[PDB]
Image (cartoon, coloured by chain):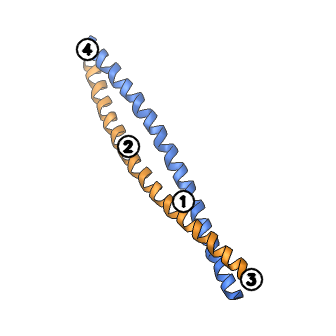
Chain colours: A orange, B blue
């Protein structure tokens, strides 16, 4: 029991560390997605202006 | 000691599950960001083409 308890505690702590790293990774990805979304929506505004001018011309 | 074994195993399981969930979410968001990046490049091309066309017009 003692040996197995030791090993289980060790591996669980390992998993905890990996999970924290995953948290940080997810934060990075979320920020970058926000950036790309802003770029795309502004791009859409540009396309709207493009098409409107094209129609007029 | 056995009571301690119970607690150790259970906390290990909690950590492992959370790690799994965070990993999956990271995967999904990363893939979406990559796709939108490709689309941002695509619309860069589209705006260039639009500038050419509006000039000719």
Circle nearer the viewer, 3 or 1: 3
- How many neighbours does mark 2 have within 10 angstroms: few (below 14), some (14-19), or many (20 or more)? some
Q: Look at 71% across and 83% down and name the residue there.
A: A2
Q: Secondary structure at mark 1?
A: helix
Mark 2, residue position: A37
Q: Which label number is shown at residue B55?
A: 4
**Residue B36, above or below B1:** above
Q: Are marks 3 and 2 on the same chain?
A: yes
Within-10-Å neighbours for mark 1: few <14, some 14–19, many 20+: some
The answer to whether marks 3 and 1 sit on the same chain is no
> Do pointers 4 and 1 mark residues of a single chain?
yes
Q: Nearer the viewer, residue A48 or B50?
A: B50
Q: Is residue A46 left or right of residue B25?
A: left
Look at discs 4 and 3 and give the one toward the viewer: 3
The secondary element bearing badge 3 is classed as: loop
Residue A25: percent from the left, percent from the top? 47, 54
Helix, strand or loop status at disc 2: helix
Looking at the rendering, which quadrant does residue A24 occupy?
A: bottom left
Q: Which residue in the structure is indicated by mark 3?
A: A1
Q: Residue at label 1?
A: B22
Q: CA distance from mark 4 to mark 1?
A: 49 Å
Please indicate whether residue A5 sits to the left or right of residue B29 in the image: right
Viewer-nearest residue: A57 or B9:
B9
How would you rate the neighbour count of disc 4 (Cα within 10 Å): few for under 14, some for 14-19, many for 20 or more?
Answer: few
State the image quarter where residue B22 is shown: bottom right
Q: Is residue B38 left or right of residue A39?
A: right
Kindly identify the residue that appears in the image at 55 percent across and 68 percent down.
Answer: A16
Nearest to the eye among marks 4 and 1: give it.
1
User: Do the CB atoms of the residues marked 2 and 1 lie less than 8 Å apart?
Assistant: no
| Residue B16: quarter of image | bottom right
Task: Give the mark toward the camera: 3 or 2.
Answer: 3
Same chain for mark 4 and mark 3? The answer is no
């Amino acid at each position: 029991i003692e040996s197995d308890l030791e090993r289980a505690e060790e591996r669980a702590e390992l998993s905890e560390g990996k999970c924290a790293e995953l948290e940080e990774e997810l934060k990075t990805v979320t920020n970058n997605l926000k950036s790309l979304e802003a770029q795309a929506e502004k791009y859409s505004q540009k396309e709207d202006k493009y098409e409107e001018e094209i129609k007029v011309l």
